[PDB]
Image (cartoon, rainbow over all chains, first blue to last red):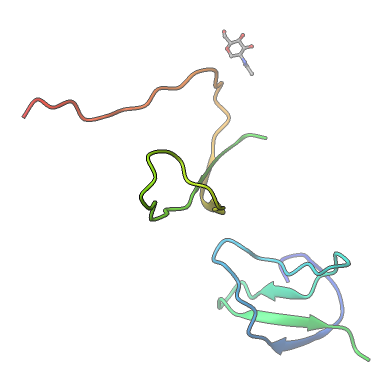
Length: 49
Length: 50
Ligand SMILES: *[C@@H]1O[C@H](CO)[C@@H](O)[C@H](O)[C@H]1NC(C)=O
């Protein structure tokens, strides 16, 4: 996604992304949500179990 | 860092003569490719000359 590279499961989530926000950093400062450049959708990033 | 950033958050101020207590989060509103030298500024208001 837009140069940011990694592995995970892209599952649709209900996170309330404000229009300016793009990333989804967590408590431990871990990427957990990204916005698709083509269509504005909030996708939850989750590593494979 | 060569950027002009403006943040705004419109709030319905209640019956307080001055800036009220509480909190308000100024959301990002626009970002522009700027970098001209900045030292001073001035506001503009409409003078009553109708
Ligand atoms: C902006 O202009 C002032 C006044 O001449 C000058 O002292 C200052 O160095 C300038 N700043 C930059 C970043 O060019």
